[PDB]
Amino acid sequence: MAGWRTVVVNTHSKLSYKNNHLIFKDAYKTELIHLSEIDILLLETTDIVLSTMLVKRLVDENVLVIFCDDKRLPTAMLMPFYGSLQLGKQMSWSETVKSQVWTTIIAQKILNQSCYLGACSYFEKSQSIMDLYHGLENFDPSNREGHAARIYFNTLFGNDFSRDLEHPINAGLDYGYTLLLSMFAREVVVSGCMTQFGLKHANQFNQFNFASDIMEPFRPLVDKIVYENRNQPFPKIKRELFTLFSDTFSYNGKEMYLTNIISDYTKKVVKALNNEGKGVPEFRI
Amino acid sequence: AGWRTVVVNTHSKLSYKNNHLIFKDAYKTELIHLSEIDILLLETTDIVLSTMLVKRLVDENVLVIFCDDKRLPTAMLMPFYGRHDSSLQLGKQMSWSETVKSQVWTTIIAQKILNQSCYLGACSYFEKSQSIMDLYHGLENFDPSNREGHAARIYFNTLFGNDFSRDLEHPINAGLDYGYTLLLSMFAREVVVSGCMTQFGLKHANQFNQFNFASDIMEPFRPLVDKIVYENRNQPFPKIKRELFTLFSDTFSYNGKEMYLTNIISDYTKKVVKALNNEGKGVPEFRI
């Protein structure tokens, strides 16, 4: 909604493509918008027709295209099959630098998990996580991050909450993470990096491997909303997750829209990896 | 059989009414019961469709694929979450023990490693094939010493050489990436059909992975893509894409018969889930 240029279509209309423009037609007007200016196209209602030529050009320009549920909330997106000299730069990232940056980013997440428990006054649990953060070693082979998560999620949602199907906590958390992931994946593509190669995981295929790394510190933005709505039905949880995209968050001194923060953070992680691990950005809640 | 696939490649309109996909071009009108479609391939750039149709396609778990100017997959519809009628299988998935998940995972990964050896053998790299074979025999639960990674390093280096060769000299990693995503889309669909969440896998948990479980299940099938890419390693990327795009209508050997890859994926996925539900027993097997 906010930050990134977002075109919202929610009325009875036809979308087409001509001469580098998105073309919108309804009974009242025609609108033309240069595709290079769109970051997100949100198709909110069920009375829109579009062409596959438009779809093809949208995907060529890395526009995030999102189709919605019966309540006008994000529910599917276009996902490309294969998303500057960044490629050669990336091939030059040493193991040491990669492992370092990965560790620093994951540490941010563990820190944010501790901080959020702190904001909820779970101080004992919070400390326990802070201790895991301070103990974190390169690549975290003893899986401190997992221990921290087990503490974090059990404290927020109760023990064995994954077995309680009457509260859709995991669907809620995953929905949020998918929204975050959609935007990080876009910024990774735009950076020029190879998207399937991240900083640590090599065995299992993940088409969003690198984005999945970079998004890590942001996940507690979602945790918090789902926690605040932990006794609500899924549609309500989805509606509240959507409010991320129009709130501001504090970052690098200022209050900024999430989309802009994602774009800045991603570029700076890439820049840091290109420059020996120096200047890894930070995101704090 | 082979997954009911609707191919659209003419100047047309796709709409939705009374549980039907509606197709109109200059030759015909068709009305197709939407729940009978498994894949919708939109192969040309002169198609219009409605967001009511997209919504219903997603609701019914139809794999939708959009193509570029050469009738090659360029994108798919990716739903944010799978829809299930019933949450019984979902409870089972949240209750599978670590012992049973680890065991099944290890069995599946073993099949991949075996397939990697067998393929090197078929390419006459007999020594390298045997090195992988030794790793296979050494494999232990959840592979902490990372024999899987050692095998992969041997395998990919043998077939394709170093990173320079895979990234700049030839479009190998792009090829493999394209193929693995195509293959993964089918597994993901079958995981959703089973009632499970794709995001929760058998081994990885820390980093968010949208298709985690489908990706575990695909592991033994990855050398099908490797093979097509190796066979086409000196071709341009479009030709590699074209050869890989055959996977939606390719047949292979499984349980002693020749079958469509779609039907195999659907059977193999359904049996892995049944196996996990039944203490790890009866994990299906795929061999090249």
Image (cartoon, coloured by chain):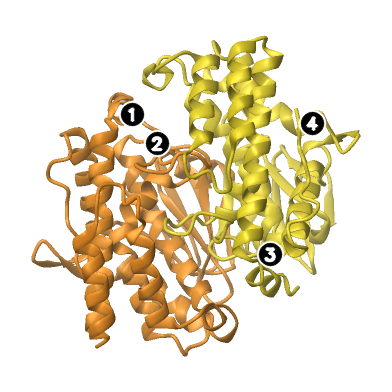
Chain colours: A yellow, B orange
Spatial CA span between label 4 and label 3: 27 Å
Q: Is label 1 in a helix, a strand or a loop?
A: helix
The residue under label 4 is which amino acid type?
Ser
Spatial CA span between label 2 and label 1: 7 Å
Label placed on residue B90: 1
Task: Say which of marks 2 and 3 sits in front.
Answer: 2
Q: Is label 4 in a helix, a strand or a loop?
A: helix
B164 sits left or right of B147 in the view: right
- Give residue B188's position: percent from left, percent from top: 39, 49
B167 sits left or right of A27 in the view: left
Q: Are marks 1 and 4 on the same chain?
A: no
Q: Are marks 4 and 2 on the same chain?
A: no
Task: Please state which of residues A254 and A82 is positioned toward the viewer in this rendering.
Answer: A254
The residue under label 2 is which amino acid type?
Met
Q: Which residue is mark 3?
A: A57
Residues tagged 4 and 2 counted as in contact (Cβ below 8 A): no
Residues tagged 2 and 1 counted as in contact (Cβ below 8 A): yes
Task: Say which of marks 4 and 3 sits in front.
Answer: 4
Chain label for disc 4: A
Residue drawn 27% across the image and 64% down it: B113
Q: Which residue is mark 4?
A: A246
**Dot 4 or dot 3, earlier in sequence:** 3
- Give residue A176's position: percent from left, percent from top: 60, 32
Q: Are marks 1 and 3 on the same chain?
A: no
Q: Which residue is mark 2?
A: B197
Rendered position, B173 above or below A189: below
Chain label for disc 3: A
Q: Residues within 10 Å of mark 4 (few under 14, many from 20)?
A: some
